[PDB]
Every structure is written in C-alpha cells, then in structure tokens.
Amino acid sequence: TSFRDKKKFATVHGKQMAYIEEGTGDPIVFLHGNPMSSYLWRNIMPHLAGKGRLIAPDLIGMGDSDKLDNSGPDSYTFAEHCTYLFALLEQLGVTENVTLVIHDWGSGLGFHWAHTHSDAVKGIAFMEAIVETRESWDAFPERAREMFQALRSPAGEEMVLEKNLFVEALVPGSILRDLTEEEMNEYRRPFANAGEDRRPTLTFPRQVPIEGQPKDVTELVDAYVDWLGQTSIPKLFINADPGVLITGEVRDRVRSWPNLTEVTVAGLHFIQEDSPDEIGAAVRDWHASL
Amino acid sequence: TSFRDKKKFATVHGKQMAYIEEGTGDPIVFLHGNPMSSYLWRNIMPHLAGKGRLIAPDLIGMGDSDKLDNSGPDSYTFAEHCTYLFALLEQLGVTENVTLVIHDWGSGLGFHWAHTHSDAVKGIAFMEAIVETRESWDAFPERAREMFQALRSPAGEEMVLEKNLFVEALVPGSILRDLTEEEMNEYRRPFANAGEDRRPTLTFPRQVPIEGQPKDVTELVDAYVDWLGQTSIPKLFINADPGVLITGEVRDRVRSWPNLTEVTVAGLHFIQEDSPDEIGAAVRDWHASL
Ligand SMILES: [Cl-]
Ligand SMILES: [Cl-]
Image (cartoon, rainbow over all chains, first blue to last red; front, top):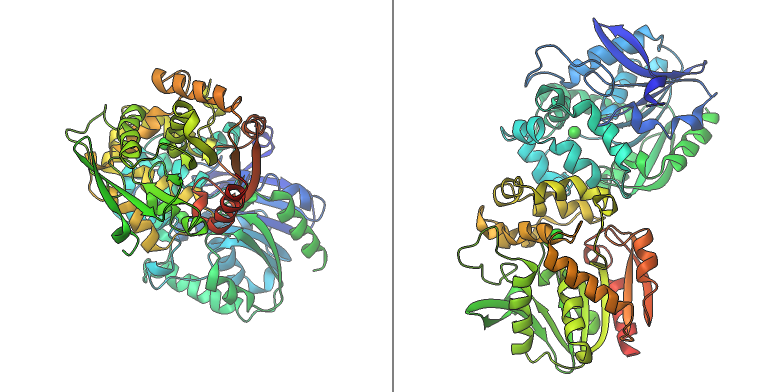
C-alpha cells in the first residue's frame, strides 16, 4: 500500500478520483485498461521519473477511484470514462506537450483524446492497444473469443458481478509469469465486493467495437485509426512477443503508421507485468528524442 | 478429422477406449492429461515414426473413449484412470522395453506405471508433469490457484459441468500462441455436452495432491517421486520456458534425479501446442541413445 499511499485525490464531477502524480514538467500520462488500475504502471513509471509530470489516473470505479451511484448495465461505458478522465485531465492542467503511454482501454481513451486534442500531443507510446475495429469475430484472438462472446450475452452479469471472471480467469491467462498473491490481491481489491463494484470489468468487454457494436465506440475508433495513419506525431509501438491483441496482420497495419519507433518485449496482453523495465527503458529512450 | 479416423478401439472393463497406434517395435507410449486427448501429441509423434510402436491412448471419459456409467463426484479419480489405462496397456501388450512420453495427469499415470513396472521401462520423457506433492497452497501456481481452489470446493460442479471452465479458461490461458478454432474445437469435442460428460475435467483438479488431500494420490505420488530420485532409468526432462507446473525450486528438485537429460523449449503448460518439433526432436535424439 506504499504505492497506494502515494495516490492523490481530486474531485471530478463530484466523484473522488485517484491518481499518481510525481514531478514537474510536461505531462507523461499513463492510461490503464480493463480490469486494471494505475498499479499496472508501478514498475514502468520510475523509468520516466524527472522526465516530466507523471500522471496515472485510476479510471472511474477502478483502483482507488469512487464507484458510480446507482450502477447498472449502462454504467461505465467508454463515453462515461471519457467524461471523468478528460475532466480529470483538464483539472490537472493536461493540455499541452502531452506524452501518452497507453494500453488496452487506456489506449482507446488515449488515442481518442489525442485525436481530439491533436495539437496538444508530443508523442504516443502504445502497447497491446485498440488499433482497429473488428468486422468479424474471426479476427478476435481465440484465447478469449468464447469468454468475450459469453460476456456479450446475459451470462456476463453472472460471470462478472458474481464470479469475477474477468479478473480471475482473463488476467492470469494473459501474463507470462505468475503474479505474486500480493499483486493479484491489489488487482482484486477494487472488485472484491460481489455485485455492482465489478461493473467496470463487464461493460468494458461489452464496449469493444465488434460488428458495428457499439456504434459510438466503432465510429470513434475508426476515426482515430484513420488519423493515426496520417499524423506525424511520434509513435512508439511496444510490440509483444507473443502478444495477444496486436499479432499477425494487425502488426503490419500498425507498422505502416508515420514516424513510428518499435521495440519488442516479452509478453502476452498485460505486458507491464512481464517486461516492465524493457518497456520503461524503451519509453524513456524514445521520449528523450522528442 | 483424419487424425480421429486413425484411432483404434479396445474394450476395457466393458468400455471402449480409443488410441492411436502406429508402427512396430518396442512401445513408445504418449500419455496426455487434463482436459486433453491423444490429439495433443499429433505434431510430436511423427518425430518418432519408425523408432518403435507408437501408442497414444485417450484416457477413459476423454477424447474418443467412452464415458463411464452413472458418472458423479466419485468418478474419474486417479485410481479409476489407472484401472482403465493400466488394463489397456496390458491388453495392448505394453509389458517390456517401454519408452514413456508423459504430461500433466499423463505423467501421474506414467510415473506410477513405471514405478509399479520398473523392470519394463526403457526411458521416461516428461514435461509439465506431476513431480511433487504440495504441502501448502502457496506452492501451487498463482496462474490457476483460485480457479483450482474453487474447483475443489462444491462450486466445482457449476464451473465445469455447466460452464466447462477448465476447457474454456484454463486451456487457452496456458498456451503461448493462439490455437485455431479447429484445434480448440477438437479439445472442446469430448466435452461439448453439459453435465457429466465434463466430469473428468473436474475430478482431475480435485485429485491434485495438496496438503495431504487426496490421501491415496499423495501417497502414490510421494512414493514414485522418492523412486524417481533413486532409479537409474534414463529420464528426459523437457523444461518449459517460462513453464507453469515445473518452475522455480521444483526445477532444482527434478534436476537432482539420476541419469537425467534436460532440454528447454518455449511454453506455458500445454507446451506441445507451442514447441511440438523441438519436443519431438529432443525425444527422438534422446531415445536414439537408449
Ligand atoms: Cl475488455
Ligand atoms: Cl488438473
């Protein structure tokens, strides 16, 4: 909890939002995805200490951030995460010369933010990220396909709200090493309570843009992907071996993007737990050249 | 289906048991574990073609072997698997000069078979195997610790018989690559029906010797581990990187066994799906020296 003690709190739309904030300078913003928190970045951030104002927010209802009132099936959508995070980013004075370091849904949020604040961005470092919409399930990793489809059905509530299956099944299956009990416990902690506390981890898989659904997210991702293909903003692609989300043909498409630096590290999906020092060193070295 | 079309059948305690059998000579017996079948060995066996009589059985209630009558909480124990497999091996004339190639519960069965038929064994090649009893849950891999704890509780029936979680969550989580939908379907096939058809995948986790339970398995595993430490029978340890079951201090213990050759291949638990040719070549070269 010495990491957890380091968190500051800010009131955003009446909700207490937790975030790490260390140092001064232009912001380097680390965005976690599902079902993680700023904790995912704990071993990467020290590699950027003194290189800027390091910020890693706990997304709404995640980490040490407050949960939403009257939480339901429509709670914790992508748009809602935007409202809270963007406002948090605004309140923290994150408006210019921003470096983004992004993963999974953190990359959905980060890419969208950069696309809509294209003049405010110094560089984008991304990994195991949302870099496409999917026309079919055929392009969705077999590793999680059945689980994800089941989550895209009424069964999801049982799996997630009652059984915590995203945290308990999907996290460890996509890390190469074993987590310590301590680490897995911190990932459990925001979601230990059965019921609505675990809602962020179910809505996220339901927000993944597949076959046009959801419409708002599909359009949103399609827009930023088109823009990433043209923008001269420096990009660091942290490729994973073997990887999960960015493998095969997706990799080829990502590699066509302009002003792109690439480093490969060992990992599946939650690659921060497998190669944090290689990731941090790569981000530091690349950032230094911006 | 050209692989399944290859299976021969034998009646064992009134039940049909399926098996691959190719070639002639001294038997080379490939034993799968949970929740798999002889299919797991399909890319490894060709490396031993013409080196002996190749035999890959489907365990009772698994692959294309029959399901047991009146299946319930007491069915498909380790003892029961021995009853069927050991009878199959006797009925196939696997009685001398036997080379074993074993994995997971296949290794529990193979190691026990070897211990109880010590004058019949030419060599034992093993990977991601049952090589210890565990004195506490802390020594069980975090990757599936909570899952296994849940499975061993009364919650097990719901997780497996209804939700088929061992096949759906635990298999893809412990292979480095993505399986094809075709490959995953073959592992799904014996367990497509909800209910007791899935019992073997539930009783197996309940049979892992942890904190002295079950008593019978703990004792037979301790007994064969003691013997493996003493026997001159040649052993090939196929170590997996990063591995799941045999990692950390477990490796050190296995490495102390006499007449042991070691090769490391990439993989998690179901390593045959990640490094079949490396495994096949290692077995072939080692077998050549026996
Ligand atoms: Cl997700
Ligand atoms: Cl098992």
